[PDB]
Image (cartoon, rainbow, N blue to C red):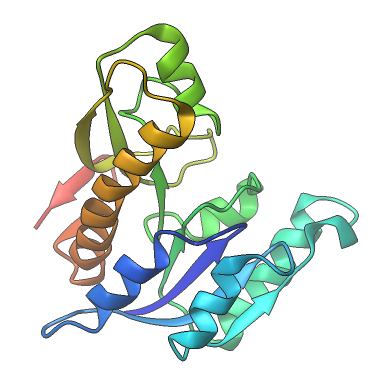
Length: 200
């Protein structure tokens, strides 16, 4: 499968995804890394790995469908089969999500359904859980609510800050995100017609 990775920041998940697609027997390859923001470290990581990049400034569009269409155009340009959201911070419009249904995955730093939203760690610390984690899920219209592919629990240590908890969780993300990409790229895991996840 030909894969596109959308990012909005440091792209901490890129290295693990990139290495994985280059290990023996990978069913995927990363052909383009797209950012909605210029000058973020994720772009350099892509370049250094020898992967083409594109910056599509969401602030230059009228609305989300417009912005999403500009992304869809590049995805078509690179005949992309699967899209991975890695620290991508723009909520996508229904038409784009429907078009990529079953082919777009996101990594989220909590054990969904708990702590949906971009400040998952802050919520975890505020709620007082001793166990949190990360989740890779197919992207649905509803934010952080698509079908779950894999999850990994991570302990929260007393005195953790957002920074320390975040770092520990990223280590789990680096394990399940690449694994989930392989499962979908190999056709091993699919979003069934009944909208439920199915393992072949």
